Image: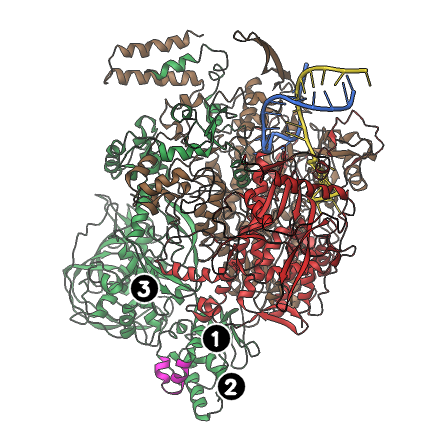
Chain colours: A brown, B green, C red, D blue, E yellow
Amino acid sequence: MDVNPTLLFLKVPAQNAISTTFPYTGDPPYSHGTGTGYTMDTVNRTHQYSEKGKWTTNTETGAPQLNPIDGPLPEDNEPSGYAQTDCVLEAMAFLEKSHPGIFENSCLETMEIVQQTRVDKLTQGRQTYDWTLNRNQPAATALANTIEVFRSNGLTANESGRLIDFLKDVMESMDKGEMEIITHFQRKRRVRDNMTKKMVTQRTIGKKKQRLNKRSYLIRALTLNTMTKDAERGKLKRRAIATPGMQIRGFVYFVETLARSICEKLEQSGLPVGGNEKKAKLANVVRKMMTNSQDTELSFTITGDNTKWNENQNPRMFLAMITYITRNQPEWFRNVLSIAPIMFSNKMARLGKGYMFESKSMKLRTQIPAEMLASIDLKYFNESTRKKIEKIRPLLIDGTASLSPGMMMGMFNMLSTVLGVSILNLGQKRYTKTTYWWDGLQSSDDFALIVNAPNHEGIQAGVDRFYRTCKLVGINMSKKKSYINRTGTFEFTSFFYRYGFVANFSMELPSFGVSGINESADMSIGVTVIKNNMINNDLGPATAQMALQLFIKDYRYTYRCHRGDTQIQTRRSFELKKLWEQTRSKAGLLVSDGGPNLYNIRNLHIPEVCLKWELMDEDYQGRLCNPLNPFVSHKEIESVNNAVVMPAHGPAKSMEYDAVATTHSWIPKRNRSILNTSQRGILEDEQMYQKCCNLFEKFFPSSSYRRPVGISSMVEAMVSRARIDARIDFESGRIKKEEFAEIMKICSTIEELR
Amino acid sequence: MERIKELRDLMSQSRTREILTKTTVDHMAIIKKYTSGRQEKNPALRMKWMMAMKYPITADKRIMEMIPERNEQGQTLWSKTNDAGSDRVMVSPLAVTWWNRNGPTTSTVHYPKVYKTYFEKVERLKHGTFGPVHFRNQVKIRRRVDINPGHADLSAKEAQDVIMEVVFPNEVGARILTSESQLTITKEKKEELQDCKIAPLMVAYMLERELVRKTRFLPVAGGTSSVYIEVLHLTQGTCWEQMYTPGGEVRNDDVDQSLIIAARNIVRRATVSADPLASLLEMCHSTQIGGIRMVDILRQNPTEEQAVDICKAAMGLRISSSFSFGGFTFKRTSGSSVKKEEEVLTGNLQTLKIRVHEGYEEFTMVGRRATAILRKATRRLIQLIVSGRDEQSIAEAIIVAMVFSQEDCMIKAVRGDLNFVNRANQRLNPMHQLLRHFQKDAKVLFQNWGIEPIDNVMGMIGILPDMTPSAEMSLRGVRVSKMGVDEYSSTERVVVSIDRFLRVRDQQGNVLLSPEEVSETQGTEKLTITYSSSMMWEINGPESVLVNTYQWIIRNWETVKIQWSQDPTMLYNKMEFESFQSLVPKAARGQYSGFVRTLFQQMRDVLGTFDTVQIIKLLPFAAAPPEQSRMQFSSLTVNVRGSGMRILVRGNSPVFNYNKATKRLTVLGKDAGALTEDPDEGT
Amino acid sequence: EITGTMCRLADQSLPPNFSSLEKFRAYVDGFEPNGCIEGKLSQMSKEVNARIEPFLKTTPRPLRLPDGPPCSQRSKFLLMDALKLSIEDPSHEGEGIPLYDAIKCMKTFFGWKEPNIVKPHEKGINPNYLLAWKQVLAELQDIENEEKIPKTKNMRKTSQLKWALGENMAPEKVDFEDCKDVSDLRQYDSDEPKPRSLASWIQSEFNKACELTDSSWIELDEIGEDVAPIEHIASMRRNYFTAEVSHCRATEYIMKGVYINTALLNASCAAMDDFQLIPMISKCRTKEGRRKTNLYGFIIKGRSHLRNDTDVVNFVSMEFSLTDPRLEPHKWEKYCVLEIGDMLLRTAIGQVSRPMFLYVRTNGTSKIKMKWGMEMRRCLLQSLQQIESMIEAESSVKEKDMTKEFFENKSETWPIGESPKGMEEGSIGKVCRTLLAKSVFNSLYASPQLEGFSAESRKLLLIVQALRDNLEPGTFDLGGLYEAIEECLINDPWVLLNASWFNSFLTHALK
RNA sequence: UAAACUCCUGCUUUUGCU
RNA sequence: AGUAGAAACAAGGAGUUUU
C-alpha cells in the first residue's frame, strides 16, 4: 500500500508530532563560494525598502549614505524602513509609563558595569574583523594587534587596564592621519653546514612600514566584514552575517549591556535568558490574557513573524532610543552609549571575497577580489549578478559599500527587541482607549501576538492598528509566514504551544554525541547533554537511554576504545586484556580506555571517574592519580570546564560540565595551514612567547587563576616581586642567607643588559 | 632561587625576549588567550577528522623524556615535529594508551578530598533510596532555583576572596577583610591543602566551585533544594513522577521551613473542605516530605508555627502558652486581666462586641518582622518599646498594638463598615475585622492617637503619624528603639483543644490560633512536598484544578456512577471535588450546590434523563453545603485567575467544552481523557 | 568628549533637519507624547493594512509540483535494490578487517560472467566504467593470491579511472590579469537548478524502507542496571522500540550510511593522494542470533584534498543489484549498469535463476556530507522522540502504566496508508518505522530544498490543524505562502515527494 | 618552453608586503 | 563526467631539469 507519514497528523495534533517536520538530521546547507553575491543582494535590498530618504554625503568618509527615517510614510504592504522619530520616542515614552522608572534605573547598573570592566571583556567572543590585516582574526589577536597600533602610534593612552580609555583613544585614533601600521613580508637567507659541507636556505620574515589617511583609516574603522550565515536551517537562500570591526564592539558591549538590562526588567523578551524562562514567559501571557476574559470576548492570537527584520531597522532610531532611555543621565555616560549607533549609521560593509571566473575555452579559473568591482568589464558577469552591481556601483567606496540604513546579522540584537516590545507595550488597555487591546512577546524577529476585542470587527480593527503601528518604526511583519487563530495555538521561535502545554522542538538535536573537545571531557559533556536536555529541551526517559546508548557507540568509534569482551580489533586490543585479567574490579574500569558502561539515567550528573571510583583496585586509579599529567596542560578558569557548543537560539553558548582532571583531557591539534601563508610571522615570533609568558606566570601563584593587572614591563614586573620575595625569605626561612646573596646578584645583572 | 636564572638566561639572546620586556600588563593579560588558531566552528567534524590522522593529540615536550617511542605492538606512539604555536609536540592516542597501562603510579589518598563535591553526589546516590512511580501529570514550574551553593552562603566575589587567601595570601587586595564567621572556616581550609598532597593550584579552585551559588532557571516539578536539584531529571516527567530520597544528612534548620509550607497547603485546603476536623488528619497519613512522612517530623519539632501547631493539635499534641493576634507571637511577662463583653460604636456607628481585658498587663510583641514590648491597661496602651527591621514593620507592630489596646480613639477612627467576611459559611471576630481595616489605611488612626513630647536619653526615639522618627515629639506611649528589644523568653507546652472550625482553645477557652491567624505568605519548597491524593492540583494552578478534576471523573466513572446512584453524600464529600470548591463563587456559595443536588434529585426521580453530559458537568458543584435560594441559579460562574469565566446550563462553554462526535472533553482548551461509550448507550 | 572627527559624523547620524547632536540630545529631553501615534495613522494610507481573509476548508489549493523530466537517483548508494553477498557467521576466515571480509563474499558467489553494459551512461564515457570494474575485479584478486597481507588497498591511476575520479579536470588557478581577453571568461553557472518532476520510484523507495526484514540490524551498547523504577519503565519502553527498529529496513540504510561515510572519512584522512578501494559492508545479526557479514559493493575513493569544509571527494560507487535498469529507466540517469553474474533463487512454488547487475556511478561527498552520514544514528533518536512524546499525549489519558497500553493491543489507530480502500490505519510498530523511514531520507536526500520547504510547509501544516480543530484560523496572504513553497520544490526526489504527500494530506485533512 | 620528480598543507587557502 | 545550487569543488602551495 502507499505509505506516507505526514498523514499521522490526522490523528495526532500537529503541535504534538511537529518534530517529524524538522529535517535536522541531514546536513545543514552550506554556502560554497562567497557572500559577495549575498552582501550585494542585501545592500540592494536595504536601499530598496528605504529608497526615499535623503541621500547625504558624509564629510570625513565620502560615503554616499542614505538617511531614510522620518521620511515619507509607506503607502503599501511592501516592507519599509521609514521609521518615525516622533513615534520611536513616543512608543517608548510609553515604555516607562507602564513599567515605571526603567531607564534611569537600568543605566545605573550600566553606569557601574562601565566602572568596573576591563578590556578583557571584549577579547572574548566570536572572531572579529581587525582593521590591521583586513581579515577575520579571532577576538584575542585582533585586540592584541590594534593596541600596539596605538603603541606604534604616538598616543597610546590606553594601557590603564580599563577599556574606557581604550574607548577614548579609538575616538582619538580618528584624529591622527599618519597611522603607521606594521607590515611583515617573507624573505629568504643563506647559511652553511659544517658537518656535511652543504649550503642550504632558511626562511625568515621581514618588516615593512605602511601608512593610512583619514579617508582610509575611518573606512577601515567603520568596516563590517560580511560572511555568509553558514549552517542556518529553514532557508533555501542564504544571508549575510556581519562581523563587526574591532573598534565597534567596544562601544557595542555597553549598548547591549544596557539593552539586555532593560529586557530582564521587562517581561516579554525571552531573549536575555535561555529557553526555559521563555516557556514561562510564553505561557505567562496566555493567562495574562485571561485576566480580563469577560463573558463574551474574542481573543485571537497571531503567530507573527517579521519579514526583512534586519534591513528595515536603522541605527538612526537606535540613537533615538538610547538618547531617550538615558534621560537626565551624566554627560559622559550618554555620550559613550551614543557612539555605537553613530558608527553603525555610517557603517561600510565589505563585499566579501569576490567571484570565481571560468574559461570555457582555455579551461582556466581565476578569482578577482571584491575591490575590483568598481572597475570591471561588466560582460564578465551573468544577467543576475550584473543587475546587482549596477544598483550599488555608486555605493562602492574603497572596496566597501556604504550601508547606513539597516542592520544585519551577527552585529547586535536586544535593543531593536526593546523597540519591538515597546509597540507590544502600547497595546496595554490604558494606552489604546478603545475596545481592542493586545499583548505578546518579541524575540529577535519571530514574535507572537495575542489581541482581544469583543467581535471579529474589533480584532480586525485591532490587528491592523498594531500592523500600522509597527509600520511607523520599520517593523514589517511577515504577511507570508504568519497567521491568526484563537488562543492556545501558536509558536514563538519554534516553541510550539498546544492548549497550554508546550512542545519545545526548537534546537532539536544537532549534537547528541561526540563533540570532541578532549577524550574524557567530551564524555563528561557528552552525558551532560543527555542530562541537560532531559530538563531544558525535554527528551524523555527512553530516548535518554537511547541517546546515551548510542552516544557511547560513537564515543568508541572516534576514540577506538572498544571493550576487551568484544574481541574486535583496532590499534590496540591485547594490553587492554592486561587490565581485564589483573584487576579484580573488572566491571569498574574506565570506559575511555575500554570499560563497561555503568552510566544510566540515575547518574548522569556524576562525572565519569568519580562514578568509577568506589570499585577500582588501587593500581589503576593510582595510575590515574599521577598529577604530573603530560596530557592535560592545566587550563585557565575561562577554559576550565567550558566548551563552546552552538544552539539555534543564539550565535554561541558556553556550557559547563563536571569534568575531573584525568589523563584523557588532552588538547587537540592546532591547524597547520598558517605555515603556508605569507602570514607565517604572526606565529614564529609569537609561538616562542607563550613558551615563556607562562614561565613568568609560575612566579605569580594567582596569575593562572586571576588576571594579573599591575605595572607594565613583565621583565620589570617579576623583579619587583623578586625583591619582596627576597626580604620575607631573608627575615625568616629555611634556605641559607648566603644563597640569598645569589638571589640578590641576578637583579642588577638583568639591568646590566641596559 | 634557580627559576630566576632562566628569567635572565633568555635575555642575552636577540630582541625576541626583549619585546617581552616591552609587553605590557595588558598585553600579557590578553595574549594569555592569544590564538593564532581560531576556535573551531564545528569541533565535532574536526574530532572525526583528526582522529583518523596518525597523530591527533598535542602532548607537551615532557613525553619525549618519559615515554618510549617504541612499544611492544608495532606502532609509533609520538612524533618529533612541533605543534604550530608551541614547543608542544604531537602524539598519538597510543601515548594515552601507554600512560594508563604503563605510566607512573602515585597513591594520593586525598585525591577524593580534591574533588569532594562529586563524591558527595555518589554518596547521595548509592546511599539514596528510590520510591515507586506516582503516575501524575507534569505541571512544571520554571523558576530560578539554586544549584550547589555550599557553605556559609557567601557572596560570589567573597567566595573568591577566601579562595584567594588559601591559594597564596599575598594577592588578596581585599579592602573588606572578612566577617567573624569566615575567620574560623578559612583556618580549617588552611591546613587541608597540605593535608591533600604537595598540591597543585587546581585543588584551590575546586574549593571555589563548591562555594559558587549558581541559580539556574529549570522546570522544577517538585522540591527545589540543593540536594534535589542535581538530580531533577531522575524524578520528574511525563505521565509520571519518581519519588526519590537521596541519602546524607537531612538538615536541621529548614526541614522546619520544608514543613511549614507543606502545612499551609493542607490548612488552606481544609478551609475550603467541608471537614477540616477530619481531612487535615486524613491528609497527614498520605503526605510525604522527602519520603519521611509528616507524621514522623511533627513530633520532634519544637518550632512554633500557626499552621504547624494546628497540624500538631489535630493529632493530639500540645502547643505553647503564647497567644497570637494578627499572626504575631505575644508573650505575657507580667499582669493579668479578666474578660468583659462590651459593645462599642465605631466611626460608622457600627456595634462591635469586644472582650475588654480589665487589668494592667505587660506583653512582649514579637513578630516575623518586629519585636516589641506592650504595656497594656484596661482599654488603654500604657507604654510600647518597639523594634523592627524597617518602618513598615513598625507600621504593622503599632497597628496590631493600637487595635488590641481597644481604645476609644482607635474605635472612633474607623472610616466605613467592616465586611471582611472571609471565604466561608460561618463568620469572623471584631478583633480581626479591626486589624485589616487599619492595616489597609490607618492615617486617620495615627492622627486621632495623640502626640506627645519625648526625651531621647539612650537612643529611645519616637515615631510620628507620617511614619517618621522624631527625637522631639512622638505618638503617645510608643517609643522606637535604635537597638533590639530584649526578649529571651521560653514558653512551656500545654495541652490545648481544637474544634472543627480550627479554633485553637486553651484550658480556659481562650482562642489561641485560627485560620484567620494563618499568614498569606506561600514560600518556596525545599524538600519535595508529595501528596498522595489530589491536593497538588491547586499548587499546579487554578487552571489545572478545573482540568484534572474533570479528568478524574472519567477514569473512575464506574466508581462514580454507583456512588451517583446509591450514596451521593459519599460522592459529594470526596476531598478531590473540594479542590474545585476553592474556585466556587462566594456570592453563589451554596447556591450552586443547592441546585445541582436537586437537579440530580430531579434526574434520580425521572429515571430517563441519564445524560452523562450534565452529570459530568455539574457534579463538582455539589461538594459545597447547599442552601435555599430563589429560582435564579443558572449563570454558573467559575473563577480562573481574576476573571469569573462562565459555564452555561445547556450545551458547551469555553470553560467546559464537550464534543459529541469526538467524545473528548475540552476543558479550558486542554483535552481531558476519553470517556467510554457505555454511559452514552444506556439509560 | 567627542573629538573633531567623530562629532562631525555625529551629525549625519541623526534624523533629517537635525544638524547637531547636542540640539538633538536637547530635543528628546523636552519630549512628551502629544498623541502622535494616531496623528500619524491619520496621515498614513488606509491601504497599508493587514486584513485577514478567513481560511476555510475550501481555501487551501494544493501545492503545484514542478514540471520537467522525471527525477534521478541521487542517494550515494543504492537503497531498495542492493544485494547481500553474505558470508554467514564469521568466526575464522571472516576476520575483523573489511577488505578480507570482501574477498570471502564473492568467493562464495559462484556464477560470474563477462561485463557487458546493459544501459549506458547517457553523457559519460561508457567503456571507462567497464574497464573500471575489470580493474578492481583484477585488483582485489591481487591480494588473495599474494600473502604480503595488506590492510587497505590502493588502486593505481589508469586512464579510465583518472576520468571517473576527476583527475586534473580542475581548471588551474591562473591570475586574472594573465588572460583577461578570453572571449568566454565568465562568472560560473549561477543559474537556477533545472527542474525535475515526481516519478513513481521515490515513493517505492519509501515503501520498502518502511517494511520489516528478517535481519536484526542494530546491536549496540549496554547501560547500567535498572534498579530504579524509571530505568525499569524506560528500558521496557526502549526494548519495545528496538523490536521494530532492529528489524526495519531503514536501519539497513543507517548502518550502511554510517559505515560508508565512516570509511570514506577515514580513508580521506590518510590517503589524500592515491585512489583507495573501500568495500561497503553491513553486518546483520539475524532473528535467532547467528551473525552475518553482508557485502554490497565497492567504492574507489578519488583524490581527497579537502582544503575547505565543502570541497568534494569524488568517488565511484560499484553496487551489486538485481533490478533491471530497463524496467524503469527514468531513475538511473546517473548510472552505468553492467551485468556481471547470475544466481539461483528459491520460489515458494518452484525455483528460478535470474541475472545480476552492477551499478557504477561517479559521485561526490564533501566533508560535511560524510560527517552527517556518521551522525545518521540520530535518525533513531528523532524517530524515538515522537513515540516518547506520543506517550505524553497519552499521559493524561490513562495516568498509569502505558507502555503496556500500546504494543500489547494491535489497536491499529494511527493513519499511515493511502490505498484504493481508503486511508489505512496502522499499529504503532508500523508507525515507528515510517517515522524512522522519514527520518532517514531526511539525511540521505538532504538538500537545501528540504530545509526551505519544511520551514514554510510547517506554517501551512499548523493552520490546517487549527482548521480541523475549529480554531477559526486566518492568514494574511496565503497565496503568497504558496509561492514560498513552490519556490523551493525544484529538483530533488524527496522534497517533490514530501509535497506530494502534503497535497495528499490536504485532500484528507479537509474531507 | 613541455614533461616528470622533490618538500609543506587539509577550518586559517578570506590577502598584505617586498 | 560528477558533485552541487544563485557559487563552488573537480588539490592548493614550493623546487628542479629538457624544441
Q: Mark 3 falls within which chain? A: B
Comparing A67 with A30, the one in front is A30
Residue at the disc numbered 3:
B264
Give coordinates of residue B664: x percent, y percent: 52, 75
At mark 2, the secondary structure is helix
Query: What amino acid does circle 2 point to?
Result: Glu
**N-term-proximal mark, 1 vs 3:** 3
Amino acid on which disc 3 is placed: Arg
Quarter holding residue A630: top left
Label 3, secondary structure: give it.
Answer: helix
- Is B176 positioned to the left or the right of C90 in the image? left
Indicate whether B50 appears above or below B482: above
Q: Position of residue B435 (x, y in %)?
A: 31, 64
Q: Eyeballing the image, is A568 above or below B324?
A: above
User: What number is the disc on residue B637?
Assistant: 1
Q: Which mark is residue B681?
A: 2
